[PDB]
Image (cartoon, rainbow, N blue to C red):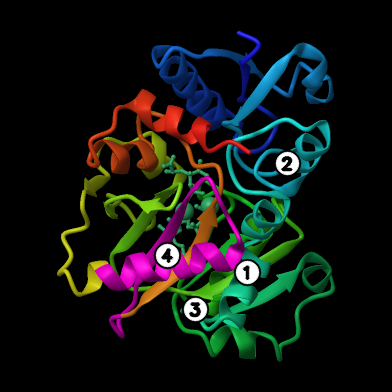
Amino acid sequence: MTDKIAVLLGGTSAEREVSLNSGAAVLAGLREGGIDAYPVDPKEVDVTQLKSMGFQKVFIALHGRGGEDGTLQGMLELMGLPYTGSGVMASALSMDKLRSKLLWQGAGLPVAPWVALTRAEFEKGLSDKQLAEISALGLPVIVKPSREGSSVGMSKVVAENALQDALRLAFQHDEEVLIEKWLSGPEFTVAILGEEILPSIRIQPSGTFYDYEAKYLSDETQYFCPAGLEASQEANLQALVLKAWTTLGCKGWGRIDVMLDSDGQFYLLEANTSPGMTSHSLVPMAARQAGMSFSQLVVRILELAD
Ligand SMILES: Nc1ncnc2c1ncn2[C@@H]1O[C@H](COP(=O)(O)OP(=O)(O)O)[C@@H](O)[C@H]1O
Ligand SMILES: C[C@@H](C[P@@](=O)(OP(=O)(O)O)[C@@H](C)N)C(=O)O
Ligand SMILES: [Mg+2]
Ligand SMILES: [Mg+2]
């Protein structure tokens, strides 16, 4: 009461249905922890009248462009309403897998060899002396849109012969594209809550990459918590994820994706400042393992709102 909280779910991104799913969970979780939370889909109500509706705080359960970029966060800062995750800048920074990679590399963090392409570069026919670039990377490479989540628009390409199509796809999602080198090793994610970092997770998709379907609609993908890593490695991770996190300037809560490569090093893929919270999500998995309940987690996240 007074402390009527708003749970921003839905929205209009490509990740809209996961959001609705993440949002449904945070709702019950919060209400279970005794909070007066309400579902607010920006694809209906105008978020601008948020203040005019008496919400004292906001829990962002939106994913992608519109909710995980600096926009929403910018407005709220001006409305003077506390909200759950990272600030304007770090939400802007994280969404952009391209500027993320440059900043992380600027700070000496291990980021995978890549090539960036804009759509106009693509519409004109890319320089034969540009596949010189993509080729100096390896076979295979992965194509990903710059500002997406949930493995949307991504595609793996073996041989330069399938790239034109990979790129067609990725471009339907963003005008800026990264073409990066295939990491050949196990995959990992690390959740952060306040200044604590949750037991690590190792994912084992039952396919080629951790794809939208592996992520949410497949009961074959496998999860290990913690990671099953020697205590040497399990320390290189945390320290890396933490260096990574502060470099972005992120706060409150979020989750970082990483992978091993053949040379035995950890490579940073991207950071997510508003992680999913569905029955398949990773943040909730890492938290349980750390003895919290779905409501404690979410409640703790709200406690962190600024
Ligand atoms: N360099 C890479 N090599 C191999 N697979 C990768 C690479 N980068 C990402 N992937 C796979 O693609 C999935 C999407 O990765 P990620 O970059 O975090 O994007 P998104 O925001 O869509 O989740 C990852 O979880 C991983 O399974
Ligand atoms: C699987 C993962 C998804 P997500 O948080 O992260 P990715 O960007 O890698 O899909 C996503 C909502 N953007 C989760 O719900 O735990
Ligand atoms: Mg992501
Ligand atoms: Mg990911």
| Above or below, comparing residue 269 to residue 82 in the picture | below
| Pointer 2 residue | 73
C-alpha separation, residue under disc 2 versus residue under disc 4: 23 Å
Q: Which residue is mark 3?
A: 109
Q: Earlier in the sequence, mark 1 or mark 3?
A: 3
The answer to whether 177 appears left or right of 118 in the picture is left
Q: Amino acid at mark 1?
A: Leu
Give the SS element for disc 2. Answer: helix
- In the image, 64 versus 158, the foreground residue is 64
Tell me which corner region of the image, top left, top right, bottom left or bottom right, holds residue 168: bottom right
- Real-space CA distance between mark 4 and mark 1, rounded to the nearest whole angstrom: 21 Å
Label 1, label 2: how many angstroms apart (C-alpha)?
26 Å
Q: Which residue is mark 1?
A: 178
Label 3, label 2: how far apart the Cα atoms are = 27 Å
Look at mark 4 in the image and give the residue it sits on: 241
Magenta residues span 235-264
Q: How many marks?
A: 4
**CB at mark 1 closer than 8 A to ligand 1?**
no
Q: Which sits earlier in the primary sequence, circle 3 or circle 2?
A: 2
Which is more N-terminal, label 4 or label 2?
2
Label 1 SS: strand
Q: Residues within 10 Å of mark 1 (few under 14, many from 20)?
A: many
Camera-near label (1 vs 2) is 2
Residue 277 makes an appearance in the image:
no
Residue under the point 70% across and 55% down: 92
